[PDB]
Image (cartoon, rainbow over all chains, first blue to last red):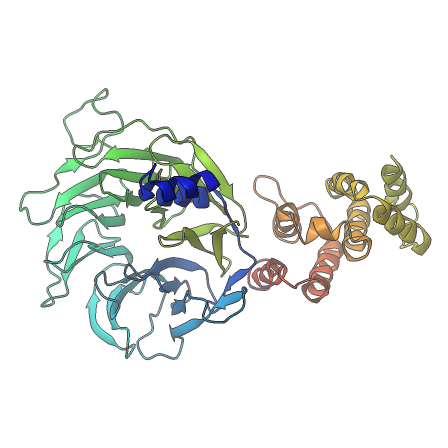
Amino acid sequence: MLGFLSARQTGLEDPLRLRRAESTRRVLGLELNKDRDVERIHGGGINTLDIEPVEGRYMLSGGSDGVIVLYDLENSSRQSYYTCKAVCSIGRDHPDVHRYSVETVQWYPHDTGMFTSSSFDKTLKVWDTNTLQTADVFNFEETVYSHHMSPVSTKHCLVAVGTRGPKVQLCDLKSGSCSHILQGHRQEILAVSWSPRYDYILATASADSRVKLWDVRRASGCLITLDQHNGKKSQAVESANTAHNGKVNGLCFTSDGLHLLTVGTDNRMRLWNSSNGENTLVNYGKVCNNSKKGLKFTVSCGCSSEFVFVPYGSTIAVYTVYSGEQITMLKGHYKTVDCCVFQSNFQELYSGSRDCNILAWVPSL
Amino acid sequence: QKLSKLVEELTTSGEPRLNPEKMKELKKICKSSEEQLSRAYRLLIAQLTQEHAEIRLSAFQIVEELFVRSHQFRMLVVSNFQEFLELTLGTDPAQPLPPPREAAQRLRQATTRAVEGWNEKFGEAYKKLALGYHFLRHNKK
């Protein structure tokens, strides 16, 4: 490394090199920090975590018990050891607490003043962070498996919601219009994700093994259906063009938004070109999931090489996105792992699990 | 070697009782060399994976005494101990299917009491003991 410092200092390399390379080096060194803890507040498993996109200071966390906890990730104490204390919490006594498991929780991109959370009580509630009161409640006729607000839309403020119904609901937070539906799936929608590149592209994955990308502006159905083989097994599309051979319970666009990673219960992950949904044939090997609900996984950002961190049973498996090489499997949870979220500032990973723990993985040295 | 000799002399179920002289000899031997204990775990996995429940109890007690006394099993059970976390999650909880649980209920109670002791005995930064105890208390104690 001192070579890296000397290269930065002399302008041999752009300073971008040392960031990105050092960021990567940090990611490869992720290790369970016992020099950092997250305060236990969930009585039930953590289904979801979300670090705020601006300033990355606060994390939301949704539990199987229905509570939403709001954690502060900055070490405000002077010690080197700290516990990420829980700022607020939608507890059992809140009048608005969810009744059943919170399945997704998301900071409003663009501003930390409002977050949204959806549950198995069939509601997507929008919250004022400051007063911690709901500002809006959308009711759905079927249990919500995931939602997602666009990380990029300065223009629209749609929330895509996937329920057990076969239809994707778009909920407009600007005047509250929960009527719009995308129709074309056939079984529950286990994962939705807006594109980080394009304002109005949404990808939705369903238990029917199909993943569709939609231009929600468009009035004409899906843009693309991802097909495992790219056409080697080609049929008039009524049942073919499955992304997976099981349920597809996870989606994640890569950072720059040029590829889509889907995980499904055939124990595979695939990487897809998000422009024409073609399959890049990245291998990745066998990725165990048997989650019956959405599997929340992330990608890294701002490294030399992009990584994807996928819950693999009771561990987080780290893979290199574009080559498939499994970097490592981070082993520190006790029960299955439900969600991992990446802190892009410091290359830290937080992962929740059914054992009611949120473990921080920070680079060593 | 001598580790295996002591393991055979202690884990033998014909006299299934805690003998203090042999345990102190094992403590002193483990303190004399750390490499005694790294293979001792391999011996203990032999006794945990053995058919007889009394041998499993004996190997569990030996692991606990080496972790709490020798100061070399502490660096196995409170550092580089994901194997220990997984053995705690597999012993008291159900063995992963198809393979079912083979230990005795008295061994389950002994493991519960050992976990409750180790929650305070060595928990300066190893809180997954308490987390596993809570998971047992809320799922398959």
